[PDB]
Image (cartoon, coloured by chain):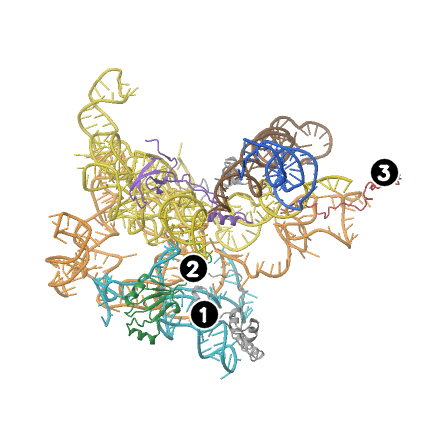
Chain colours: A red, B green, C purple, F cyan, G orange, H brown, I blue, J yellow
Amino acid sequence: GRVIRNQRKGAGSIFTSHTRLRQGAAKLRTLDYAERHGYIRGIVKQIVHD
Amino acid sequence: VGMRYFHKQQAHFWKPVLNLDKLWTLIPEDKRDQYLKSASKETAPVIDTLAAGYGKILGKGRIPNVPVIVKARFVSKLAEEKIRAAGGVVELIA
Amino acid sequence: VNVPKTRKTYCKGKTCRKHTQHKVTQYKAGKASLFAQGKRRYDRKQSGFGGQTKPVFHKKAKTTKKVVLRLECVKCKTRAQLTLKRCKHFELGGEKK
Amino acid sequence: PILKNHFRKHWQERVKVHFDQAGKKVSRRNARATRAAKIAPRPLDLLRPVVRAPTVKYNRKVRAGRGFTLAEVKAAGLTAAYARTIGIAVDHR
Amino acid sequence: GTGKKEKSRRIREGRVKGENFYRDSKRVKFLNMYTSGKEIRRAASFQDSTIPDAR
RNA sequence: CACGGACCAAGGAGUCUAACGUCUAUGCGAGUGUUUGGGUGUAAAACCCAUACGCGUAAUGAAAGUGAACGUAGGUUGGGG
RNA sequence: GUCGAAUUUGGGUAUAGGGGCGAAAGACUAAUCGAACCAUCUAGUAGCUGGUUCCUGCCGAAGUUUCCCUCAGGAUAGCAGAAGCUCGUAUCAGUUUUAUGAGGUAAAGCGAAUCUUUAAAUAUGUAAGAAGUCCUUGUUACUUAAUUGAACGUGGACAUUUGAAUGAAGAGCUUUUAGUGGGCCAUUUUUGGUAAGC
RNA sequence: GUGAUUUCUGCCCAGUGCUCUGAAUGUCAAAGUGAAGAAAUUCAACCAAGCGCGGGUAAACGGC
RNA sequence: UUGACAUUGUGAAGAGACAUAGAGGGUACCUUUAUAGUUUC
RNA sequence: GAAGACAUUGUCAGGUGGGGAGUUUGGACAUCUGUUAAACGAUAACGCAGAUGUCCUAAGGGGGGCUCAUGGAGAACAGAAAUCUCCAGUAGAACAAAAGGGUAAAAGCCCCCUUGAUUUUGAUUUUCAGUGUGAAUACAAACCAUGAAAGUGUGGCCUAUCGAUCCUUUAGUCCCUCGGAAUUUGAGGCUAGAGGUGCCAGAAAAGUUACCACAGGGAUAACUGGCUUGUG
């Protein structure tokens, strides 16, 4: 027969994630020297819908 | 049917026969009559069958009374026996 | 059926050429011997792609085999084969009727 | 009778017919005249030895070989390298 | 693959066309009775159209 | 009341080849086949030719092998002339 | 039918043939989809259908045998033509007559048995001579007690009434190949069937 | 897979398909190991997964 | 998906066998021992 | 930072593998007796009533003896119902089995000896192309069995009981070949059997399509030959 539905997902033709409105990738801070041997102080500026 | 024979080449099997019927065609015509008018063991006409292109001498018909020297690679039993009736020998050339 | 262990039949071994005493045996097929001609041609042909190449016989209908009965002489030891008809129960020697 | 013809292949592509048999012969004799003017005093072919043929069927005959030897050229009294310029074939093997 | 063959299954357990790992050997003659009555151009089964001998 | 045909002109279907069988014509005949090739030329024609080679003159064997007159190449029977 | 939203639509862009895409009909993918279109392999294969082009002369069939995964077809035999060859009255014949065989059907019979005691008509086998008969004795490793016999002969004897009738555009022999291998009807016999253009 | 809501979903792990914290010497390839032989070669012992055996599972196919 | 071979090295322990290195020791033998070695799990 | 002589990657090997690829998915067939079958033979139908894919070292051979099925008249037990005995008994019994033949000093029943159910290859009969397979009959050369002897015996009293090519395997010879020349293993040959194709003159093989495709075939009912009506 023809190719069933779940075999056709992995091509990524029309199934790619909708990503126009996303703010950015939600990651922690990159582990530098100051975060590995002390602390650093940061300000939260706005909390926002993604 | 039989056994198989790998790499056959018809140069190991070249051996054309020659009946004692012919046996005088190898001598040319103008020399043919002279040795028939001689029963001499002194002068027997030498026949070299290998130069004519004949492997084996076979005895089929009967030859005249004249003694003949025959040179060949192979002769048979009745072919060699019939020449000794005429008083001729067979020299096995190779 | 029931055949005797001893049987006096004609021999041929360049000396006997007469009715001499024999001993009975039953024929059994030999070992397959994979270095024969047919096995080596069959093994080279199955090697590779293509799957099965020779026919493989399926439809069996017979229920018996022919009794093949070879007889060993006791003087010259020349063996000679001899056959019977198709039969189902084949014992030999004992149980005289 | 059974007769074996080997024509299942696409044989009509590879058919060569020799209409140039009388054409190439005329174009070959013009080579043996053009060479005979370039090689102008010289006899157009080297000198060939005398050789007895192999293979029991044919050993009764004698045949023109390829070249003489390093030995037959020495016994005639000349070197091998001077022999090829005079016009004499030399086979080393 | 090598195990799920007709020749290699019957050796594990210990002839009509269509015997499988499924139904049985006897079900194949049974379930072919739904297509049994046909005449092939051999007349159809249970209609022989012949006169027997009634003694 | 099975299929094709409205009418006219022009096209339109047992062909060529390789290996053969029976038969017939011609050449030579224990031989035969010049044309792969060479020589020659009025130039793809014609004419000439060497050594080979193919088939034939011996068969039978799976083979190693062996290999055809007792005799007017025989006796009997029927035979054209 | 629905008409503020799972709405409608322009442009841009993404997915391409055993692949796409599908709120799922095997739908749609340039009037083509239970597998697009283009060119090549390709003049693919057909045991099936249709067609096959001038005239006269002579001869002239088959639907049947056995085998085949054979039943719309092949191979084989039969029937047919052509080429002729050896010879020339000749061996003969879809026929009768004389002689002698084999049959078990209709009838007859159950005071025959339980399915034949008897036995036609029509059909059928073989003879009607020269490759014969007769006489005599030659050969042999067979045969006999034995040259006894068998078989083949040497030699001798018997002509066209030489062994019934009628007839005989010759008789014998050999190659070689075509088409056919779907049949059907009537008298008489008979099966199966109530009977049937069965 | 099923198809809002209200309401209700009983029994069977034999087959079939899964599954495993199970079992252990039943079958069991190549490679390697041992023996015989002049050698090619042959017979042996050993042998992973799977299979086989044992356990689980039915809002898994199902049989109700 | 599972096994073997290759990629693929080096250590310290352990369990063996040999090569070597002396002593003893009833062409040898063989219980012993040292070391500097080559390898087997 | 993590991990480390393991993973990864390469090559072979087993397990799984309609997710995918290619293809297939037969049309009283081999036989023997009776009858249909119409006085040689041959002769059909999805005619017909029945048998076979076996069985037996004797149920094969040879020789000697003997008479069966059945009835009548009788013998403590014992009767219709064992054994005994006589009279009649053309077979009314029996022979491995279907069926048709044939069989009485036997082809049956009992005893005596045995392996001819052997070796070598031809001729012939049946189906038939007068090919094969099967089965059968009569001889010749051996070597045997048996019988006092003639004779008989090449399986079963006659008609049914079965199998090519390639491959595997044994027996025969102790032979032939391994092609540079020998030895020893190994392999291939000539001769004669076996292992089997029951679709039995011999392919290795599951379904569905109403989504269907193609090349072709075949329809049309209602006049049999007085064919149909009211009386089982």
Q: How far apart in space, not on screen, are marks 1 and 2 (Cα)?
A: 42 Å
Q: Residues within 10 Å of mark 2 (few under 14, many from 20)?
A: few
Q: How far apart in space, not on screen, are marks 3 and 2 (Cα)?
A: 99 Å
Write the residue at 43% across / 65% down.
D57
Give the numbered dot on residue C72. none
Q: At which x and y percent is residue I22?
A: 62, 37
> Under tag 1, what secondary structure?
loop
Say whether residue D69 is visible: no
The reply, left or right, for residue H23 in relation to residue G108 is: right
> Under tag 2, what secondary structure?
loop
> Under tag 3, what secondary structure?
helix
Residue denoted by label 1: D62
The reply, left or right, for residue H27 in relation to residue G128 is: right
The disc numbered 1 marks a residue on which chain? D
The one of G3 and G125 positioned closer to us in this rendering: G125
Marks 3 and 2 belong to one chain: no
Kindly identify the amino acid type of the residue bearing the numbered disc 3. Answer: His
The one of G162 and J219 positioned closer to us in this rendering: G162
Residue denoted by label 3: A37
Point out the frontmost of discs 1 and 2.
Answer: 1
Figure check: G51 above or below D37: above
Residue denoted by label 2: D2
Q: At which x and y percent is residue C37?
A: 46, 49
In the rendered picture of this protein, how many numbered marks are placed on residues? 3
* Quarter occupied by the N terminus of chain D: bottom left
Kindly identify the amino acid type of the residue bearing the numbered disc 1. Answer: Val
Residues marked 3 and 2 touching at CB (< 8 Å): no
The reply, left or right, for residue G31 in relation to residue G183 is: right
Kindly identify the amino acid type of the residue bearing the numbered disc 2. Answer: Ile
Marks 3 and 1 belong to one chain: no
The disc numbered 2 marks a residue on which chain? D
